Length: 48
Length: 48
Image 1 (cartoon, rainbow over the protein chains, first blue to last red):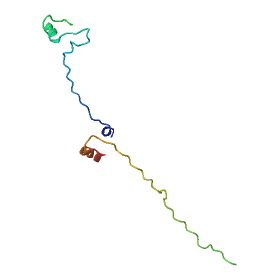
Image 2 (image 1 turned 90 degrees about the vertical axis):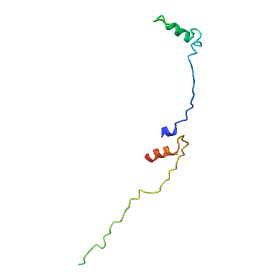
Image 3 (image 1 turned 60 degrees about the vertical axis):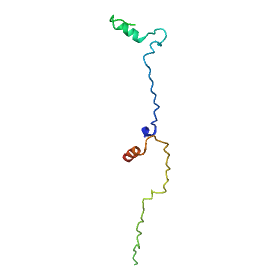
Image 4 (image 1 turned 180 degrees about the vertical axis):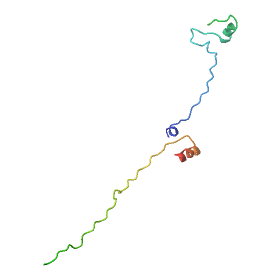
C-alpha cells in the first residue's frame, strides 16, 4: 500500500556531457584530450 | 394433628447473552490517487 500510494512519476533528463570539458576542467589543470592521448601513444608510463 | 406440606417450588428463569448491544457504524476514508491504471489495481486488490 505504501508502494501504490506514494510512487511518483519520474521526470526524465537526457544529458550529453562529452569529454570536451577537460579543456574547461577547473581552469588550473586544463588540456586538450586528443592531443594529449596522441602524446600518450608513445613514450610509455608517463602521466599528466 | 394437622400436616404441613410446601406448595409450588418456583422454577428458575431464563437468561441470554445480552452482551450484544448497539452497533457504532465506522466511517470510511478516502483514497487520494494512484498513477497505475485499473487492471493492475484489480490484480492486487483481489489478492488482498
